[PDB]
Image (cartoon, grey):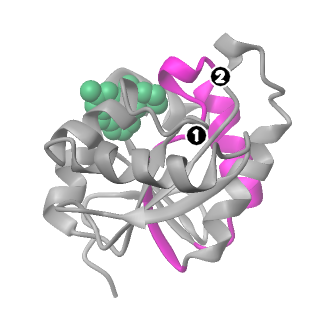
Amino acid sequence: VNSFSGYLKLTDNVYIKNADIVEEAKKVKPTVVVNAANVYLKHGGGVAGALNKATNNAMQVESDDYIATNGPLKVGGSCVLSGHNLAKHCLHVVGPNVNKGEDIQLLKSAYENFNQHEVLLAPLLSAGIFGADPIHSLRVCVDTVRTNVYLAVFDKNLYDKLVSSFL
Ligand SMILES: O=C(O)[C@@H]1CCCC[C@@H]1Nc1ncnc2[nH]c3cc(F)ccc3c12
């Protein structure tokens, strides 16, 4: 038993809700919140900009030190950093950005990072400003992640299309 509430169950291990991930994180304080990161951990907009704003820019300060030490992530890769006031940990995961011409096959590799964590609160990778089809992203999520994933979908209209079209 865990503290996630109001989710619809899609599969044995995948759950979905219409929610603002920032507010969902603030209330649940999950062990892991996933950020829709880029390779530079520049949290300017989308999910990343919202999460970072909710940390009063502490996520960005920590991220800049991480990059200065380690260099950029790989597309499809991830790193574990602090969850600040939102979660114990933040798993920064880089899905391919279709608006940068990145290979969508890397979306499966991106979701594989979730399997290193028993339970996660997450957005749909490569959705939103990353330019991928959120229905495809949901399919890859279901077919790749084996751990327990609670997906927060900000847009109510999108949440309903994702549910109604789910196979
Ligand atoms: O659902 C959507 O509209 C999109 C799905 C994936 C790409 C961007 C959006 N992502 C999110 N997903 C969950 N919570 C969120 N809070 C947010 C707050 C913001 F200021 C911007 C985006 C989100 C967001």
- Quadrant location, the N terminus: bottom left
Judge by depth and name the residue closer to the eye, 71 or 103: 71
Number of residues whose C-alpha sits closer than 10 Å to that of mark 1, classed few (under 14), some (14–19) or many (20 or more): many
Mark 2 burial class by Cα count in 10 Å: few <14, some 14-19, many 20+: many
Q: Residue at x 60, y 17 (%)?
A: 131
Q: Residue furthest front?
A: 69
**Residue 163 locus on image (x, y percent):** 50, 38
How far apart are the two marked residues, 1 and 2, measured between alpha carbons? 8 Å
Q: Amino acid at mark 2?
A: Ala
Q: Position of residue 156 (x, y in %)?
A: 31, 27
**Residue 32 picture quarter:** bottom left
Say if disc 2 is inside 8 Å of ligand 1.
no
Q: Report helix, strand or loop for mark 2.
A: loop
Q: Where does residue 98 sit, x and y in percent of width and height?
A: 70, 17
Q: Residue at x 32, y 31 (%)?
A: 49
Res 155 seen here: no
Q: Residue at x 65, y 38 (%)?
A: 95
What secondary structure is marked by label 1?
Answer: loop
Which of the 4 quarters of the picture holds residue 113? bottom right
Q: Quadrant of the C terminus?
A: top right
Tell me where the magenta segment starts and ends, as one range: 118-147
Q: Is residue 56 magenta?
A: no
Asked if residue 53 lies left or right of residue 40, the reply is left
* Nearer to me, 127 or 91: 91
- Residue at numbered disc 2: 132
User: Mark 1 touching mark 2, by CB under 8 A?
Assistant: yes
Amino acid found under the numbered disc labelled 1: Leu
Is residue 140 a member of the stretch shown in magenta? yes
The residue lying toward the viewer, choosing from 58 and 91, is 58
Q: Which residue is mark 1?
A: 125
x and y percentages locating residue 57 in the rendered image = 21, 41
